[PDB]
Image (cartoon, rainbow over all chains, first blue to last red; front, side, top):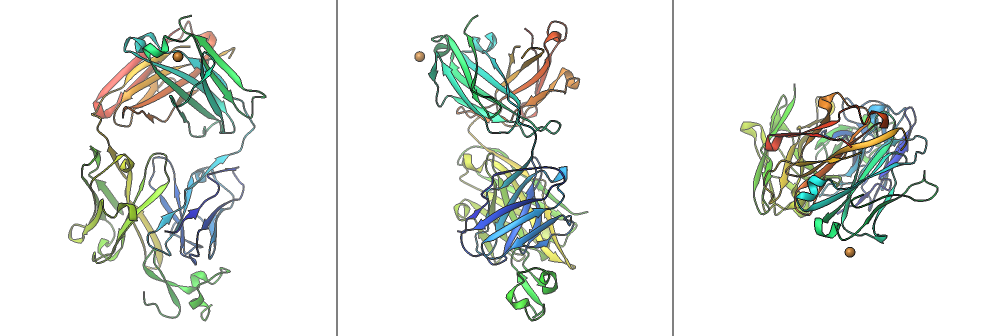
Length: 213
Length: 36
Length: 215
Ligand SMILES: [Cu+2]
């Protein structure tokens, strides 16, 4: 099965700029390559077929090029509505295969996260589980690292995080990480700490609290 | 698929496509060389 | 107006079966090849397969060829996807499509998408817990925990509070239940005087919960 490699899972751009998304086939696919667009909560949209030919209705600012193994989708004069995810596809061989996708995002000035930590609520404790939540708010770029520490011991495998889509008004990201413990485990320890690494922080910032205080 | 000499088959759309659409490209199908 | 109308997904347990429908109108369905693709959480677009007009050719993604059956009934202008032996990996949005070239134009049409969730969990509304409240800015929120299936909606002060609100994508917990947080930043000086309530709606369970969040 042919692997279609989009080496850039994210690309940083600006409204008005030219952007090119690359896609490399693991073996020759002649010109049998399509490009698709997809936004969150929307159906995909076909953009290009035959490596360079637009589907009906696709704006002229979308172009495609390439033949053999290297293919490129270009958007001239990017519009806000073009901020989305782009997928290449080969149809030289069955099974048709998609690339992993390239998500466009907007450049802005670097912004450190504001970090907030929330102890579990008494209501939740009554039910026998503790959720400790750490919030990294309105930062840029998206890459950020959160570590949990319980009485200064590095935690592993008991947290989950998720990240918002880039903010439509200020181009920042926010991240929440949830540490989940049983009420019993929670009450065996005192200090609960969220340590954050980010380009905007000249050294890692820690927010913490002491249980019941 | 069977296409006339001025067309070529695209198997995503499963249709014969006019070569003329590909002439401006640096890389048209080999069979479109005669027409382009 | 062209319409690929999808129906027939929803909740199913692992090992179960589901038949998705994609009913076309506004095009000559019978002339065209039809496709299925899906998009699973945290994954890119995945091709499932395609079927030609008279059903004599059907191609599948190799991993799906023994689970999924693609068929069509041209007399009903309808495309089907029969899913069986389903697993967590099959939880996804499923899209039907027609890609074709006719009347001198390359055309693509897509269904609106069908959600499938594969799980042993039963439908359950969330428990909502306060995230109680830097300098002049404070952060507060609601932890919307242990619901099934997706989605929940969260508003603040019945829609009156929208600036600074961030509602995160849910995470699927090891329990099979979903959890998410909704936060908002507000002036610290407002904390004594302004009421903050998150309104949490879960249509699958027909539940609505309001949670006042205070210091
Ligand atoms: Cu311990």
